[PDB]
Length: 290
Ligand SMILES: COc1cccc(Cc2c[nH]c3ncccc23)c1
Image (cartoon, rainbow, N blue to C red; front, side, top):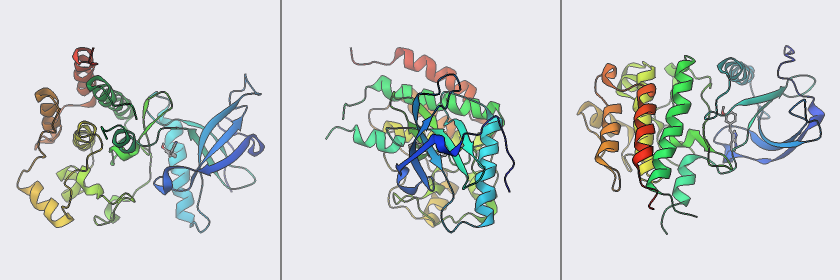
């Protein structure tokens, strides 16, 4: 049933499947070892992540996983996104092979580095924002709107590189359940721009608003936005023009950046291009401590 694409296909026997990854937040995904991923080095093994359909998947689940893969083929490569590396589409279940992120999602990474391993410098945190802003600038330049940019959808590699995940996910925005929670217990509506939340209008500008929430997540080291606030109350806060408080140990400039990202008028928010330039400059002048 699936079309062959020699640009991406890996023989099924080259992939040694392993243990589950991401505790189900990204669907059925496992760690694997791929033999001879690079055609130049056929005797090298690479740790990779591998997405597949759950046992009782419908035909729409298959379509959605295919869309995701094709979206990823078109978007191209970037250091700060989770890149496609291959696929097994023939004679067997569909496998979508992507880059492996050994240090987990950014929320977890930050939480484990709180003072009670190695604590993060002010520069490491800004550097973190910068890398994510870079991934997003690239995605935006390729006409991709994320729709759920958040710390949970940012993965961290063994070398502390931030990579945006799930940027090509299929989703029917007219059928979102605003009350559904992420497995960790939070509500995705808390990262959504008002225009996306009330009028279902997703744009690069609404992704920029989500980035503001993510900046707040970085500077609270994995803090939870609007803790205890249920959906109806969140709407009321948004309608009243409410904005989250400045995190402690966040400069006035970075708080102002968050606020700009939460501009009530979408046209007035910065773009990712501008955010990358601003963050580059702030990284250069932020203390590593020494
Ligand atoms: C494009 O983003 C994706 C696509 C497929 C799967 C995933 C989850 C994932 C990829 N690499 C990982 N490494 C560790 C934990 C989860 C993951 C993200």
